[PDB]
Length: 219
Image (cartoon, rainbow, N blue to C red; front, side, top):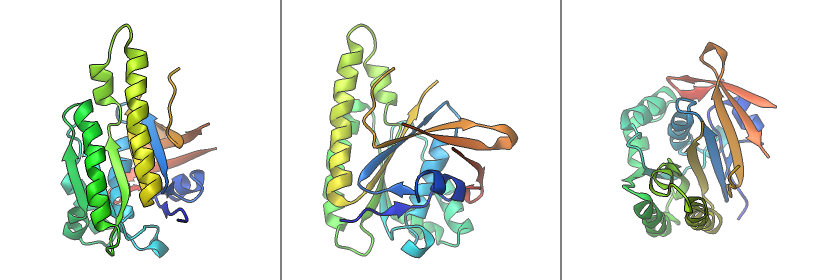
Protein backbone atom coordinates (compact mmCIF):
# COMPACT_ATOMS: atom_id res chain seq x y z
CA UNK A 1 0.00 0.00 0.00
CA UNK A 2 1.12 3.56 -0.80
CA UNK A 3 1.62 5.64 2.33
CA UNK A 4 -0.89 8.27 3.34
CA UNK A 5 -0.36 11.63 4.99
CA UNK A 6 -2.37 13.33 7.74
CA UNK A 7 -2.24 17.08 8.20
CA UNK A 8 -1.38 18.24 11.72
CA UNK A 9 -3.50 21.36 11.29
CA UNK A 10 -0.37 23.54 10.93
CA UNK A 11 1.04 24.32 7.48
CA UNK A 12 4.42 24.98 9.10
CA UNK A 13 4.51 21.63 10.88
CA UNK A 14 3.17 19.81 7.82
CA UNK A 15 6.06 21.20 5.75
CA UNK A 16 8.61 20.13 8.37
CA UNK A 17 7.15 16.62 8.21
CA UNK A 18 7.26 16.38 4.42
CA UNK A 19 3.52 16.76 4.02
CA UNK A 20 2.06 15.55 7.32
CA UNK A 21 2.18 12.50 9.56
CA UNK A 22 2.81 9.27 7.61
CA UNK A 23 0.97 5.99 7.70
CA UNK A 24 3.19 2.90 7.90
CA UNK A 25 5.33 4.81 10.41
CA UNK A 26 5.57 5.62 14.09
CA UNK A 27 5.95 9.35 14.73
CA UNK A 28 7.10 10.21 18.25
CA UNK A 29 6.69 13.69 19.66
CA UNK A 30 8.78 14.39 22.75
CA UNK A 31 9.28 17.38 24.99
CA UNK A 32 8.68 18.76 28.43
CA UNK A 33 5.37 18.85 30.26
CA UNK A 34 3.24 21.50 28.58
CA UNK A 35 4.99 21.45 25.21
CA UNK A 36 1.73 20.61 23.41
CA UNK A 37 2.13 16.88 22.70
CA UNK A 38 -1.41 16.02 23.77
CA UNK A 39 -2.88 19.01 21.93
CA UNK A 40 -1.23 17.75 18.74
CA UNK A 41 -2.65 14.27 19.39
CA UNK A 42 -6.15 15.71 19.85
CA UNK A 43 -5.81 17.72 16.64
CA UNK A 44 -4.60 14.72 14.62
CA UNK A 45 -7.53 12.65 15.90
CA UNK A 46 -9.80 15.19 14.18
CA UNK A 47 -7.72 15.87 11.07
CA UNK A 48 -7.45 12.21 10.06
CA UNK A 49 -11.25 12.10 9.76
CA UNK A 50 -11.26 14.74 7.01
CA UNK A 51 -11.38 13.70 3.36
CA UNK A 52 -8.03 13.42 1.56
CA UNK A 53 -8.26 16.71 -0.33
CA UNK A 54 -8.54 18.46 3.05
CA UNK A 55 -5.57 16.64 4.62
CA UNK A 56 -7.26 13.61 6.18
CA UNK A 57 -7.65 9.96 5.28
CA UNK A 58 -11.40 9.45 5.89
CA UNK A 59 -10.15 7.45 8.82
CA UNK A 60 -11.14 6.43 12.30
CA UNK A 61 -8.93 6.54 15.38
CA UNK A 62 -7.78 4.30 18.20
CA UNK A 63 -6.51 6.07 21.31
CA UNK A 64 -4.62 4.45 24.20
CA UNK A 65 -4.43 6.87 27.15
CA UNK A 66 -2.02 6.22 30.02
CA UNK A 67 -2.46 9.50 31.94
CA UNK A 68 -6.23 10.24 31.77
CA UNK A 69 -5.49 13.22 29.50
CA UNK A 70 -7.92 12.54 26.65
CA UNK A 71 -10.64 15.20 26.62
CA UNK A 72 -13.75 14.38 24.56
CA UNK A 73 -14.88 18.01 24.68
CA UNK A 74 -11.57 19.13 23.19
CA UNK A 75 -12.19 16.76 20.28
CA UNK A 76 -15.68 18.18 19.90
CA UNK A 77 -14.40 21.77 19.99
CA UNK A 78 -11.67 21.20 17.40
CA UNK A 79 -14.11 19.32 15.16
CA UNK A 80 -16.83 21.97 15.30
CA UNK A 81 -14.38 24.81 14.69
CA UNK A 82 -13.06 22.97 11.62
CA UNK A 83 -16.56 22.45 10.21
CA UNK A 84 -17.04 18.83 11.31
CA UNK A 85 -19.86 17.38 13.36
CA UNK A 86 -18.44 17.09 16.90
CA UNK A 87 -20.40 13.98 17.84
CA UNK A 88 -19.59 12.08 14.65
CA UNK A 89 -15.89 12.88 15.07
CA UNK A 90 -15.92 11.73 18.70
CA UNK A 91 -17.80 8.53 17.83
CA UNK A 92 -15.01 7.51 15.43
CA UNK A 93 -12.42 7.47 18.23
CA UNK A 94 -12.11 4.14 20.02
CA UNK A 95 -10.75 4.98 23.45
CA UNK A 96 -9.00 2.86 26.07
CA UNK A 97 -7.20 3.67 29.32
CA UNK A 98 -4.05 1.64 29.95
CA UNK A 99 -3.56 1.05 33.66
CA UNK A 100 0.03 -0.22 33.54
CA UNK A 101 2.66 -1.08 30.94
CA UNK A 102 1.57 -4.72 30.60
CA UNK A 103 -2.02 -3.65 30.01
CA UNK A 104 -0.78 -1.05 27.53
CA UNK A 105 0.98 -3.82 25.62
CA UNK A 106 -2.12 -6.03 25.60
CA UNK A 107 -4.26 -3.12 24.39
CA UNK A 108 -2.09 -2.75 21.29
CA UNK A 109 -2.60 -6.42 20.51
CA UNK A 110 -6.31 -5.96 21.22
CA UNK A 111 -6.45 -3.00 18.80
CA UNK A 112 -5.74 -5.38 15.91
CA UNK A 113 -9.21 -6.88 16.32
CA UNK A 114 -10.98 -3.59 15.68
CA UNK A 115 -8.51 -2.64 12.95
CA UNK A 116 -9.37 -5.84 11.07
CA UNK A 117 -13.09 -5.29 11.67
CA UNK A 118 -13.01 -1.77 10.19
CA UNK A 119 -10.45 -2.40 7.44
CA UNK A 120 -12.94 -2.59 4.54
CA UNK A 121 -15.49 -0.09 5.86
CA UNK A 122 -15.61 3.49 4.61
CA UNK A 123 -13.75 4.67 7.75
CA UNK A 124 -10.91 2.22 8.44
CA UNK A 125 -8.58 2.92 11.32
CA UNK A 126 -5.94 5.34 10.06
CA UNK A 127 -4.48 6.73 13.29
CA UNK A 128 -3.42 4.97 16.48
CA UNK A 129 -2.37 7.26 19.34
CA UNK A 130 -0.44 6.15 22.42
CA UNK A 131 -0.31 9.03 24.91
CA UNK A 132 1.94 8.51 26.81
CA UNK A 133 4.10 5.79 25.26
CA UNK A 134 6.60 5.82 28.11
CA UNK A 135 4.97 7.01 31.36
CA UNK A 136 4.11 3.54 32.71
CA UNK A 137 7.46 2.10 31.61
CA UNK A 138 9.27 4.94 33.41
CA UNK A 139 7.25 4.41 36.60
CA UNK A 140 7.60 0.61 36.69
CA UNK A 141 11.14 -0.08 35.44
CA UNK A 142 13.47 1.95 37.64
CA UNK A 143 16.84 1.36 39.30
CA UNK A 144 19.85 -0.82 38.59
CA UNK A 145 19.12 -3.19 35.70
CA UNK A 146 16.02 -1.30 34.62
CA UNK A 147 17.57 0.36 31.57
CA UNK A 148 18.04 -2.93 29.71
CA UNK A 149 14.72 -4.39 30.91
CA UNK A 150 12.69 -1.28 30.08
CA UNK A 151 14.33 -0.79 26.69
CA UNK A 152 13.72 -4.44 25.76
CA UNK A 153 10.04 -4.33 26.71
CA UNK A 154 9.56 -1.00 24.94
CA UNK A 155 11.29 -2.40 21.85
CA UNK A 156 8.74 -5.22 21.78
CA UNK A 157 5.86 -2.77 22.25
CA UNK A 158 7.19 -0.59 19.43
CA UNK A 159 7.66 -3.68 17.23
CA UNK A 160 3.97 -4.47 17.78
CA UNK A 161 3.05 -0.90 16.87
CA UNK A 162 5.27 -0.93 13.77
CA UNK A 163 3.57 -4.13 12.62
CA UNK A 164 0.10 -2.60 12.94
CA UNK A 165 1.24 0.57 11.13
CA UNK A 166 2.86 -1.40 8.31
CA UNK A 167 0.35 -4.23 7.94
CA UNK A 168 -2.82 -2.13 8.08
CA UNK A 169 -1.60 1.21 6.64
CA UNK A 170 -2.01 3.21 9.86
CA UNK A 171 -0.17 6.24 11.23
CA UNK A 172 1.00 5.54 14.77
CA UNK A 173 1.51 8.72 16.81
CA UNK A 174 3.10 8.48 20.25
CA UNK A 175 4.05 10.98 22.95
CA UNK A 176 7.02 10.94 25.31
CA UNK A 177 7.64 13.40 28.15
CA UNK A 178 11.34 14.36 28.31
CA UNK A 179 13.02 16.94 30.52
CA UNK A 180 21.28 8.88 25.70
CA UNK A 181 18.60 6.19 25.31
CA UNK A 182 17.89 4.43 22.02
CA UNK A 183 14.53 4.95 20.33
CA UNK A 184 12.92 3.02 17.49
CA UNK A 185 10.20 5.37 16.27
CA UNK A 186 10.30 6.08 12.54
CA UNK A 187 10.53 9.85 13.06
CA UNK A 188 11.12 11.86 16.23
CA UNK A 189 9.88 15.42 16.66
CA UNK A 190 11.13 17.58 19.52
CA UNK A 191 8.47 20.02 20.73
CA UNK A 192 9.08 23.01 23.01
CA UNK A 193 7.54 26.28 24.12
CA UNK A 194 8.60 29.43 22.32
CA UNK A 195 7.80 33.10 22.66
CA UNK A 196 4.32 34.50 22.23
CA UNK A 197 2.71 31.24 23.33
CA UNK A 198 4.07 29.51 20.24
CA UNK A 199 5.28 25.95 20.09
CA UNK A 200 8.40 25.07 18.10
CA UNK A 201 9.02 21.71 16.45
CA UNK A 202 12.33 20.25 15.27
CA UNK A 203 13.11 16.90 13.67
CA UNK A 204 15.65 14.75 15.48
CA UNK A 205 17.78 12.65 13.10
CA UNK A 206 14.61 23.95 10.08
CA UNK A 207 11.89 24.39 12.67
CA UNK A 208 8.14 24.71 12.47
CA UNK A 209 6.20 27.17 14.61
CA UNK A 210 2.53 26.87 15.55
CA UNK A 211 -0.08 27.99 18.07
CA UNK A 212 -2.62 26.05 20.13
CA UNK A 213 -6.04 27.47 19.30
CA UNK A 214 -9.74 26.67 19.23
CA UNK A 215 -8.95 24.73 16.03
CA UNK A 216 -6.43 22.55 17.87
CA UNK A 217 -3.17 23.70 16.39
CA UNK A 218 -2.54 26.02 13.46
CA UNK A 219 0.12 28.42 12.23
